[PDB]
Length: 49
Length: 29
Length: 144
Length: 96
Image (cartoon, rainbow over all chains, first blue to last red; front, top):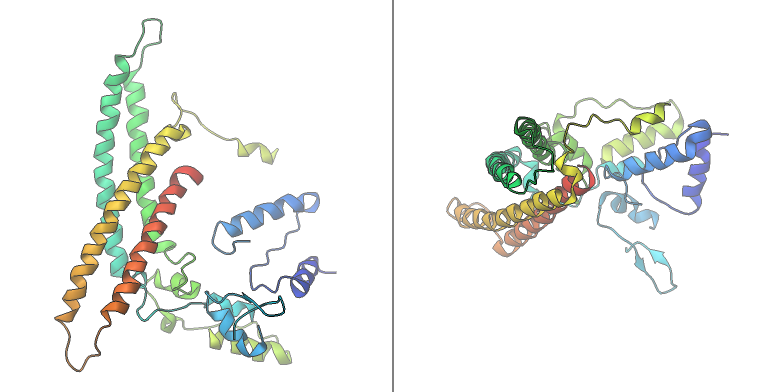
């Protein structure tokens, strides 16, 4: 039921990465807020993909 | 990575995966 | 133990120069000078260009407020100076460990204030009284 | 209309130089040179310091692998060069 369990399962089944996991709840706009989050995260050295 | 290697693989920022004999992507032991 | 990798680092025989604050000192004030001289050099370029745009002026073109144009432009070189300053400051104090294979992000963040892992005094644990989360936590922070 | 403020700006009588790509060109390749000369200058400093640490060497101290120490150190100046490059590239194209 957790919003980030989706993300978790992605990592437990495909990408076995120790990368970041910032998972957002921006209601109707989460998908963009998500793009933003990944964007910032990448431009701060946290991740490259 | 085999479990044996894990701590090391995590801690060395260079460690990367080499293609293997079975087509498989693995870390190197 | 994902969190273990905030101490990931492959250390060559010798510590990165950058861990040493004085090296960063050199390099910083080095660029500070390098910047100070750019500052003047730009006053020149923007000086020649002032007069240089007067001779390309048709009489159907609107006159230049030198006082205006000169203002904005100096002010700008001033800003752009400071900008460049803080920016080099950034690359030599704040972010010098950004993506460095030879500096664990922990080292980095710490060293930028003149500290090493030995200065790290207290670790607050999640320590939720569960069987495994307390082994693990110790184990991670320890290996770290 | 929170989103409106991704277009906030107070424009002086004249557009910021930076909007003009050629100005950023100048300034960038300006720093590229400025960087290229630092590169050599550092080979010097790290050259003198090589020999300079030989004369501070006791016989109870472990010998220096010049080949090693020199390697890491050049490689480093190389990295630090590129690093400085992309970094100025950053301040003049990406994040200006």
